[PDB]
Amino acid sequence: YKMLTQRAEIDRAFEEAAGSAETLSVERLVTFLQHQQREEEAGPALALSLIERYEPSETAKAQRQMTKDGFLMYLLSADGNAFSLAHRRVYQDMDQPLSHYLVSSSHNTYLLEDQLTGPSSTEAYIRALCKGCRCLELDCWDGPNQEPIIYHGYTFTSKILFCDVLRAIRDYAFKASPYPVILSLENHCSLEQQRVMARHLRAILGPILLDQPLDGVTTSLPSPEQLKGKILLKGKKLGGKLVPELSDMIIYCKSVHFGGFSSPGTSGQAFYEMASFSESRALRLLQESGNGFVRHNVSCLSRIYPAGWRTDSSNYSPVEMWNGGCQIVALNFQTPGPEMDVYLGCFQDNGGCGYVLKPAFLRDPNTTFNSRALTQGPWWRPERLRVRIISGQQLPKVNIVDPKVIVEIHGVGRDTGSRQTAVITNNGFNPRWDMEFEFEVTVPDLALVRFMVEDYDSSSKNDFIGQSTIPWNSLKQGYRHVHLLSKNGDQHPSATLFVKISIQD
């Protein structure tokens, strides 16, 4: 460990806490936990649980003390994670209408690559669901021998069977979360093949499928808690081209065209009705209607999808959409990128269940909040965040060297900013920057802090090494280790960044 561990900075901070002593007394640890780690629970109980839980040495663990070993073990642990461990469990109110949550949503889920000539696969649904995705898309078309198929219409994208896709979805639907999955159907099938679709839905999904409405739910969308272990369908509903068999299965997500906003001035889109917006239109409506849109999204679910020109399956930033209350922001889950990074980073919250409760100011029908034209309100609560990028350890390296860490704030217009550190030459094992940044965040509830590590290269553009995105209210203070994720969003086994975080009011 004289090479492995033996981190100068880990010693500097341990002594800062131990003093002259070579161990941490429950009394010296509790002080560290409250003063440094800014723990709200800092007391003897917390410190004793951390010693029992992370102290390797049994003697010190017996004499209620903490060595440099247990100090580092705790700092690399789930407890020392810059991402609130309390938040890795479902801890939010799950009894509010579906429209009060941001839902993990997939665009043209069937695709594994591009939008024109690429492959379609059940694997695409599996991967998406395993990543907590709750809203899946199925483009249904007529297939050979009365069997409906799924593929992107009028393109060379590979085709797969509707029934296969349903078996895959049935199997992985609740693997990563018990909360409801919505299947958005874009039907192009004939009346005969729609009946086939309906029969497969009922035969393959069985009881998982929400075939009937919930008693009592009549004025608003039911809650995620109420639809647990259930799958609901989104699509056109009979206004009268569509068979009763299918139409009768659309209960809370009746697909409708957007007929303008209106607010609670009695006249408009029902809670069981859902509209879709292109990324471009959504942005226009946000710039034009502002809080009208936000208010609209308190009672109705709104879907956003990539602009048509994005045939490369590229992604757009989900944040500006979320700031507007939009809950079903569909992104191409097959495409790695800061968009998906910030996307899964938001959905790492609330136990990764795919439903994240929007800030109360976004769950108020009369709210006057507007992300594009900020005023004073409970949303405006500026903090000063200081992040010290101390060291990095065992940086993943598969084409590797010269690191630099970019720290960015993703939130409302004002708060969107970024800072970066100097490049450390040829050192991924133990790079040390000891550099502090400082961001002013006016609307912390809509912000996310992203740590990004690149491989500097003057003539070839920097190579992505790893990243991690943490929602503001899940960002822990004091000394913490940021555990890096790869491009597929899979956590590198030992890649981390030792940092110190400070939020001041």
Image (spheres, helix red, strand yellow):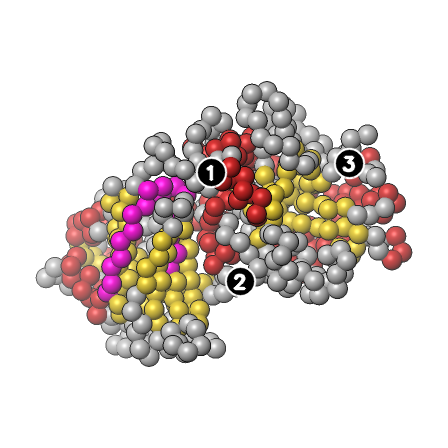
Verify CB contact (< 8 Å) between mark 3 and mark 2. Answer: no
Q: Which mark is residue 358?
A: 1
Residue toward you, 241 or 63 = 241
Residue receiving disc 3: 247
| Apparent side of residue 208 relative to residue 291 in the rendered image (left or right) | right
Q: Is residue 390 visible?
A: yes
The three-letter amino acid code for the residue at tag 3 is Ser
Which mark sits nearer the N-terminus, 1 or 3?
3
Q: Secondary structure at mark 3?
A: helix
> Residue at the location (80% across, 52% down)?
141
Q: Is residue 396 visible?
A: no
> Residue at the location (22% across, 47% down)?
34
Instruction: From the top left corner, tell me how far across and down residue 190 is, in percent.
Output: 85, 46
Q: Main secondary structure of the magenta part?
A: strand
Instruction: From the top left corner, tell me how far across and down residue 209 is, in percent.
Output: 70, 40
372 in relation to 501, above or below: above
| Apparent side of residue 144 relative to residue 426 in the rendered image (left or right) | right
Crowding at mark 3 (Cα within 10 Å: few <14, some 14-19, many 20+) = some
CA distance separating discs 1 and 2: 25 Å
Instruction: From the top left corner, tell me how far across and down residue 163 is, in percent.
Output: 77, 53
| Apparent side of residue 105 relative to residue 80 in the rendered image (left or right) | right
The three-letter amino acid code for the residue at tag 2 is Pro
| Apparent side of residue 444 relative to residue 352 in the rendered image (left or right) | left
Which mark sits nearer the N-terminus, 3 or 2?
3
The three-letter amino acid code for the residue at tag 1 is Lys
> Residue at the location (46% across, 41% down)?
323
Is 443 a magenta residue?
yes
Residue toward you, 201 or 203 = 201
Provide the residue span drawn in magenta. Answer: 434-451
Q: Secondary structure at mark 1?
A: loop
> Residue at the location (72% across, 45% down)?
185
Is 292 a magenta residue?
no
